[PDB]
Length: 51
Length: 173
Ligand SMILES: Nc1nc2c(ncn2[C@@H]2O[C@H](COP(=O)(O)OP(=O)(O)NP(=O)(O)O)[C@@H](O)[C@H]2O)c(=O)[nH]1
Ligand SMILES: [Mg+2]
Image (cartoon, rainbow over all chains, first blue to last red; front, side, top):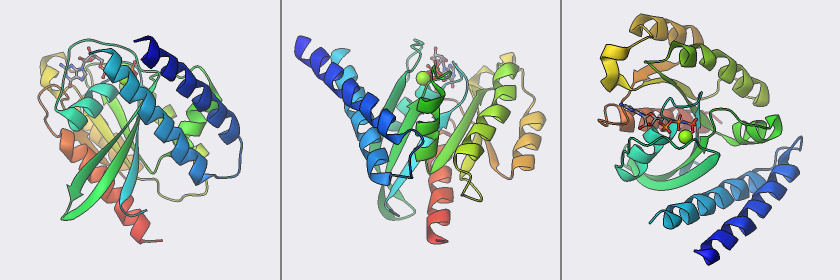
């Protein structure tokens, strides 16, 4: 589960950068789509962790 | 995109945002309570004969950072504003949640939204009279639905009805 845990950390880093990008910005649908995509990956990784 | 509808679960802690999401997504329900940070899901469904996808963003009952909350709320196309019928304070909290949604989407006129009174299986513990919640939803111009993520009562209905509101808005544009 070390591999999954490290990928969670990597995707969380990317999620934080997308929140930084989006805050106070011009409406950016492409970046919003990537935000939800990264969250979907995080959710899937955590589901795998719990069996 | 008329084939992808973006739904956000909003409401205070413990009301069943994640339970509704996971019942809808996977037909699962567990009694455990693990507070959400943020989670997201995608599902293919048939909505009135057309094959579409629903994206769901499941939020924290209380977000540490205003910017994170605003980023999530601004990205949604429609909202399920959830409270628990067993916790009156969660019902009163919906008013401020709605204001936050309206502020962050200020260029949009009528935001697709439904008020969801969850935990309808716990009728004997009700603290929110049906009439109080119905009246508030009428004042906001939205549907009120009572749900149970545990028994599946009206769970599909709230997600499909919100998708229909989003589809209506998208066609009007
Ligand atoms: N009986 C019953 N219990 C429910 C129902 N929905 C949720 N619960 C229970 O209520 C608790 C909180 O549910 P949960 O979905 O985590 O709520 P949440 O709004 O996602 N919480 P948070 O904001 O912290 O992420 C859990 O113990 C869950 O089993 C319901 O319809 N009926
Ligand atoms: Mg949750």
